[PDB]
Image: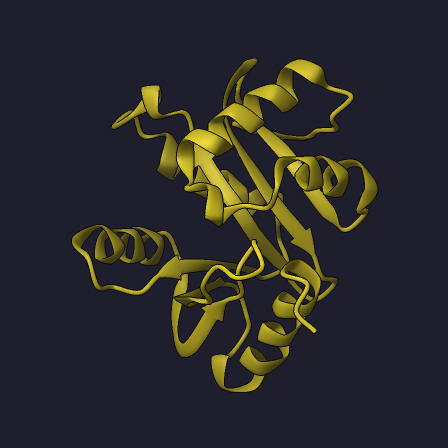
Length: 176
């Protein structure tokens, strides 16, 4: 498994990422596409990556570099590759590729699928933070989304959460 940074200059790969993104998330759950293009090539601490299994593109992951830690914004593999082991294989190498602490957001365990996602991440070495986190909306006027953060690496919720939340809301979500 291999991660490779991508620009919109990489026509085939970028379109692959973009199709898979739109098919994986509801429209309210990612930024406007024209903007996503802009972040990709314009924003230096924003990283858009295609995931390979050799030379087979199987996924994408986008993340932000915040010097102390990394924030995973979106992460998806190709749904044709279902029940094939790629989720685990990808998460495994993601922790090799990114060595500073890794932060992501998960849905709160209300539905069965939410509960499964959390145990999946916990099985693979992420700690669940029970802080009252909300994802600010991508589109002005859509809802703030109740979520939890999950962390892999040496960050303690008690000491670090407030500073991380603040970094996320202002830089990723453009609050204030």
